[PDB]
Length: 86
RNA sequence: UUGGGUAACACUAACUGGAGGACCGAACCGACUAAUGUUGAAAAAUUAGCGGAUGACUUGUGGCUGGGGGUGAAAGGCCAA
Image (cartoon, rainbow, N blue to C red; front, side):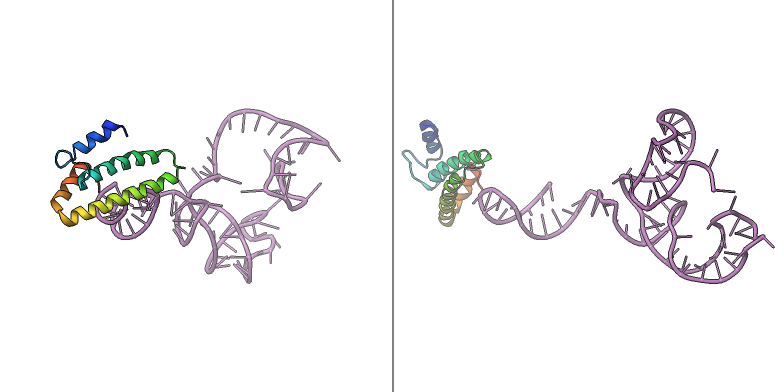
């Protein structure tokens, strides 16, 4: 993931200016990495060690969403709708 | 295929679909048990009872391979009683 590719995905999801670590921002980056990693699975079926990597990643995202939906259900439906998870 | 659960793997339910030298059975094939017949209707036939059924299947016509040769899922079976 390129620098600008990361900085841009953080800005488009950033709640406000200078928003680096937020529920929607975090999950955004994780989702991205997950996508690239999942696509990395379509190929290299043998790469088992990487499978564990995404497991932790997706687990983190699952917990982040669980926290969000639990607190603000509105920000949740919005986040998912924008990304495309679930 | 749809729905649901899962990160994925894959799972569950419903629906769809319907293969299978598969099963019971028609064309049909086979033909175990008895009597009739046995100068018989018949040089192996009749009757009751009895077994099997989309395939490497069955069948018409045409054509090929021949004598100690051929042909034979072989029984020394068949090559016009």
